[PDB]
Length: 10
Length: 4
Length: 97
Length: 131
Image (cartoon, rainbow over the protein chains, first blue to last red):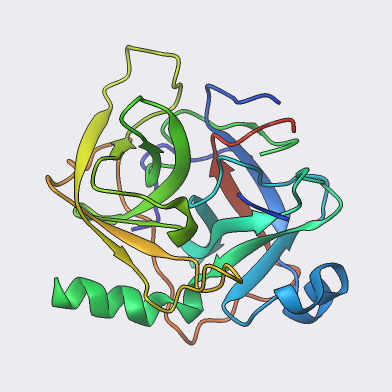
């Protein structure tokens, strides 16, 4: 869980 | 206030 | 009002319940966590979605968008269901179903 | 979200949209595994609503979204509608989500975990950007 394959960018 |  | 087609995000800080009570008084319960008052706000239609915090490399559900300012003021904290107070019930429900 | 920004598409893969029979997005939620979504109790979900996973742009028809039926709504019976306290519901899906690049689960905390005031977190959704 909790580890997106596509990383978020803020 | 209001539900969101 | 404007509803977006595309998914939005914002970073925002957690407040303490004691500090959140300066805004919301006795409306703030232990199973709530406040966040924001920081130049962003959750708003109508965000309800039920996540407030996540990154811990040891993984995003963890800390809050569930709940309620707040009826005008989504960015200077007032939003109120979220406090997942740590609720997770035992989540686990019990999954186990039983 | 007021004064947020657009997400990278697919970068919040647990985020779901709850839509009513007319296709209207009314609430968000989060996948916690392939069979279950966490949302707010006050969203008033019913088994006639749909969980939409894998979405970015609700105005696009070209996304491979998953429209998932809801088998049962498990409202936390500590929920207090008068105070909006304990505001959580679980949705048991009729058919499992198929996890992928763009569809996967958020982690849940332990009940004893500490998330300190001052920590910066993120919230996501398709709520209003202007009231």
